[PDB]
Image (cartoon, rainbow over all chains, first blue to last red):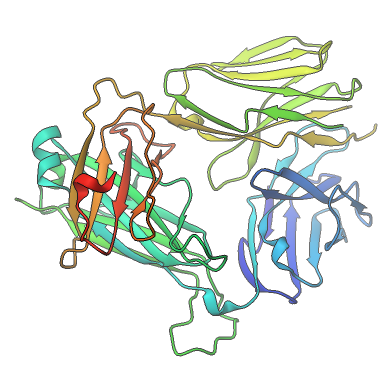
Length: 240
Length: 190
């Protein structure tokens, strides 16, 4: 396997960040990539064996360390906003050919933590008009006011995650599009049969995993520290 | 080595085929893998071809290599939501040396529902908790319908949603609009 730590991190400009990759494949070769919309996967640094590393295509701002076969670290000595990205480590064997990727680290580097906000979440109940016309019922979930822009939304029916009938916006939208600083919203739909919605013993929950500050982060404001957290909203089926 | 991958964005209706085309510069390249990256996950090798081979096929996927023109491609027959992902092609030399793996910039493939008997319609839904906080829902339109987008800093209109790639049933298109003025009717909204 290939594992990475941390999986999610929000950092401030000027701080030091270290990303760790550990492999149990006994593979000679390891790689650090970043992934950004429109730019694909770009190689930062790589290593063809313990005690060596070499510069990739975009090494600037990053150092790498390969102390052993199993470990490959990426070091940001002075984190800057353009280092906001998804980073992947990968391993491969001498003579090739598959590269085996880790699960990814999402890093956001901010100027300051004052604009970090968890989402508010609301669930909207199906329309009587939809039900009578289609025999189907769509619930809407709206997550609003969050920053930074990454959440994971999931639907839960009677305590189990569902996928059928689920449709989610591909990307969050900016609530104030004219600003660099804007907070974000995201919507998702769950569609079920009218009869399932009309049963009052069915429980529906929109869950939003938000990624924010950690527990060893300093916080000096008169509002709740916007930690990594789940925010949910829920609705019960309605008999009429 | 420079690898060109097109299209960058590929929207295809379930049941139709999808094709990604790539080209490379270095005639020494002899190894051409394809990686799939599911939403929120990591790239994973799904299929490859080498310069000794022209065509391979498995599980409804076809990979072609035209070594003379330095072109190669992936074809997914009978697309389904499970195919929605980022795809990357690559070119390498390979075999007791290592050679660079050079990736294309990626293709974001989104598979859309096949709506046989569309019945486009707009609905108003109320918050489960509060008042008349409200949203408008546009639904039951076919996947070739485009959704207009706002025009005013007080009305929010989402793009159309993308199916959960594990969805097996109840696949429909929708978009949502909401305001906070209201002062705003749903008949107008889209």
